[PDB]
Image 1 (tube, rainbow over the protein chains, first blue to last red):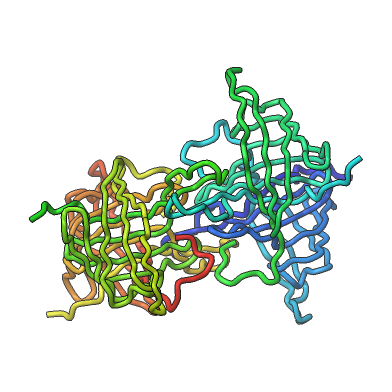
Image 2: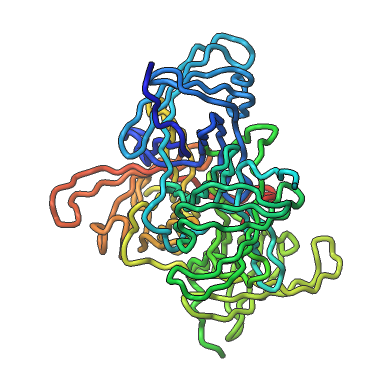
Length: 137
Length: 137
Length: 137
Length: 137
C-alpha cells in the first residue's frame, strides 16, 4: 500500500552541460520527451531540429511501489535490449518539477552480462503565464 | 454513425517555407506537438530550443462526425479566446502521415467580431527503423 | 563611379514562413550566414542544430556598381554549378537591416540551359543592448 | 620569433554534455561562432534558434607568441568587463579541428577582485563533401 505519485504528464529530458569539462555540468533541458498518460501508456520521442521528430520507445507503465514505477516496453530503438521487456525506474522528485530516474539493465543486446545502472534527469513540462513573443510554433 | 478516425497519437505541427516568397512554400516540420490520447485528452506544447518547452493548450477531445472532432478546451495561452470553450476541428487525412485541420473562431478575446477560419497542417510522429547517429537526445 | 555600399558584415539568411500556404509567408531568420569581410573575402556557412556547422561556399567579392556586387566563387556545395565562376548579386537594402539579393545563373551543373533568377533575403547581424538571460552559448 | 599559427577561420564553440553528471561530458558543438579574419578582426556571435542571431563581442586580434594570441576588445556584451581592454587567449590546437583556449580576467565589471581563468573549446568549421539532404538553410 503506497500513495500514488504524480507521474502522469509530459516530461522533458535534461542533461548536464559545461563549457569547461573540469566544472560540474549545469542542468539544461534537451530534446527528448516522455508522455506518461492517465491511462497507463508511455511514449518517448526525440525532436530533431529542422526535420521530423521520432518516437524512440513505447509501451505501458504502472507505479509499483512508493518510489518506483515499471515500464513494460514493446519496442525501444534507443535501448533495443529492452524490447518486449520490463524495466523498473526508481524515481525521486526534486524541486522545480525535476524527476531523477535510475534503472538497472542486466544484459546487453547480445545477452552478455551488463549489470549497469543508468541515470536520467527529467523536468515536468507546464503552462507558463503567457504565450511568449518571438516564439516559433 | 461514422467510423472512428485514427486521431490518437502524437502530431507535429508543420509550416510552409520558402527562401523566395514567389515560390510555393514547402512543407517542413516545426516545434509544436499535439498529444491526442487514447482516453480523450488533448495537450498542445511547444518546444523552445535551449530552454524549457511549454504547454500551450489542454482539455478533452472527441470525434463528432466523419470529418470533424471537437476540442473542449480548459486553457489555451496561444488562443485565450478559447478558454473554457469548444472548438470544432474539421480534418482531412493526407499522405505520409499528414493531417490538415481547420477551425473557425467567432469572436476575439474581448468579444469583438473575428469570424476567422484558421488552417493548420500536422504530421504523425512515428518510430523509424534505427536510432540515428549524431542525434542529441 | 559609385559610392561604396555597406556590404561588409555578418548576414543571416531569412525565409518566408506560414502555417497556412494560402497566406503569404512572413519573414523569419534561418540557419545560414554570409560573412563579407573588410578584406574582400566571402564565406557562406550553415548551422546544423545538434551537430557541426558546415561551410557551404567561399571565395572573394567586390562591389561592381551602385546596386550590385560580384562573388568570385572557388567552391560552393550548395550551388556547385558556380564552382570557379563569378556570380553577380543585385542588391537592395530595406528596413531593419534587410538586404534583398538576386542573381542569374545561365547554365546548370551539366551545362544545360537554366537561365534562371534566384532570390534571397538576408538580415544584418548586430549587437543588442544586453546579453539575454536563458540564451545557450 | 615564432611561426604564425592557423588562427584564421570560422570557429564553433563547443561544450561538454552528459545525461548522467557522473559520466565525463562528451564534446558537442554549440551555438556560438568566432570569426578570426585574415585582416586581424575578431567577431563573436551567438545564434538564437527561431529568432535573430546576435553579435556578442568584437575587436581586433593578433598572435603574440607561439602559444597565445591577444584580442583587443571594443565591446563585449557577454563579458562587459572586457570593453575597451585586451585579453590574452592561451591556445592549444588539438585533433579534428579543435582549439582549446584559456584566458584570465583580473577584475569584474565593478572593479572588484575576480582573478579567474576561463576555459573554452572551439572547433574549426569546414566544408564537407556534399551539401546534406534534409538540411534547412
